[PDB]
Length: 114
Length: 114
Image 1 (tube, one colour):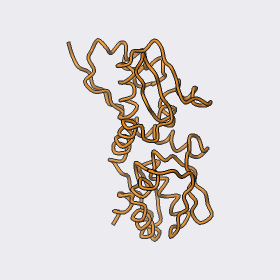
Image 2 (cartoon, rainbow over the protein chains, first blue to last red):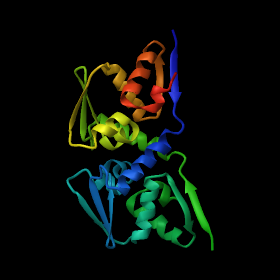
Image 3 (cartoon, each protein chain N blue to C red):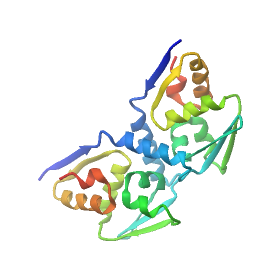
């Protein structure tokens, strides 16, 4: 008569990495985000969960969203984070800009790097 | 002239928890799994990433999958893990059974509790 609990310390990382690979190939991706003229394919369940702006958007029909006021390479970073929990070796000047796009999109961790 | 990296230690947990809540309400869920006569709503991107059996299934059309040889309450646990990275206070006798369903579904961490 006993209870067992187990935690998979590596789960989160492998999941996220599989999910990031999925979006690299468009696997299971149900939305396309267009920034400047670059198109990012992605998963609504992930963006909704992690972004208050996308949370708002995806409570209604929509397969395409067009964003302004944010550069493609900056948005690329927001996604990389959304799909890894990390920003990695970002250059110090792009930071202020990155922080702002996090603010616009409601990605708390990016918004609050300052 | 400098590079910045940041890691969000809490990201994985919040993401997973938001995702688990989503499936509790069927939000963004694109598959239904029927075990015994219980129906579980879920996300293909998550199950594909985490289960080799579902990975196989979801490379083709299909909105419903019917499983046999696995009890509902046992499958419920596999999902809870898939959506938390943890099994929590599982009773010791159900374990052997849980391990087997992990084997059938190809959920490495569950398969390898022995």
